[PDB]
Image (cartoon, rainbow, N blue to C red):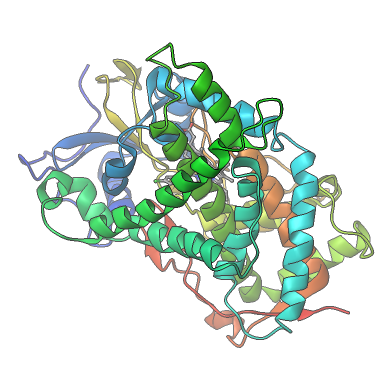
Length: 465
Ligand code: HEM
Ligand SMILES: Clc1ccc(-n2ccnc2)cc1
């Protein structure tokens, strides 16, 4: 049986000595050199199994997507989730919420259409709020978080917030700031010595007080939604959850109990707002480094969508180039370097090693988007990776930014749609430009932990006439 190869760990400390100074990801890469694609590492006491390569990630999450369908714990945030919510819940509790939220939000907009029209709309706004900026050097960080947040809030909270609404701007600002702490160094030195450090002050405390405020807003908005619930017509995700939360109060095992409502509404409100938004942020920072790549996208929009009607989702097909630039933005982006933690649900048999039940598994996704076996020139923005000789969209076994298996990003649908509608609708109406010389544009992440934060930058949105 035995666990995969890795360095011999010391008591308490685990393989802390073999760890690279830069952080976790870098470390897993420096060990893959000595052991290869699949190997074992001990983060302090807890042994994890790292997975590198496009192959290893699928042989596990795709070909045995049941023994790996288990969610692990993320150091700094377990305190607030304690295993609840739809993202961190396990076993039956997981399927319980997963299916519910996947179904609730779906037949409430998501799925397709109702949301598409919602996005073209939110985008329409993002376009007039940008005209207002009269193309003055701004910081799209906040604004971006807004447009992707509204899309999700309309599904969960049902309502939509104004771009300059103080409350709204605080949750957003809170999400951003928090993701940045969740991906900092402590958020990692914690993963290791969480039990050790938690007794002393640090950023781990700040991540708590942060999610707190949000949980409040979530919570105090559950009350508002409470006294206004017209069972004959639910308004959003909260109502539906409320209708079934009240319904099953005779089954003291129904995972539908506040704890979840808040933590699930937080999982969908944080992710739904966070990633899609910083992907575009990274996207555009990449559109300044390569202005010649923008001209094309703005031309492909011109041939297809023309320029007298907002981009529709259908257009993603007739626009194979822009599709590839996005897959490439997403690929180089790599917002989630080593995917949210996993765990085998049973004694699993993998490649010749026997991973005991409940053993944490990290699917280094970064080493799948950057894999040389599937991506020629993986470290170079190359819309080619996703195209054939006849210049058409081509699939690629290495493109797994949302991940794979039963734990695959619940919101892959929305996201891919939001990206294509916002991204083109903007480039359709505006033409980015920034004071920094393209060769000087740096894409190195500002923070790289469980998440990759693109450095902050200024960009002006010159209107196109
Ligand atoms: C730029 C877009 C996005 C990217 C790159 C992304 C990334 C991912 C990744 C890498 C995971 C972990 C998969 C795993 O367990 O191995 C995940 C999970 C998750 N994401 Fe996203 N995500 C995106 C947007 C969204 C959106 C728009 C929502 C909200 C509707 C969302 C909600 C979720 C949820 C609920 C999970 C947990 C799923 C589960 O436990 O089964 N994400 N996503
Ligand atoms: Cl702790 C954590 C992990 C993943 C996500 N996420 C973001 C987008 N999809 C998943 C949010 C929070």
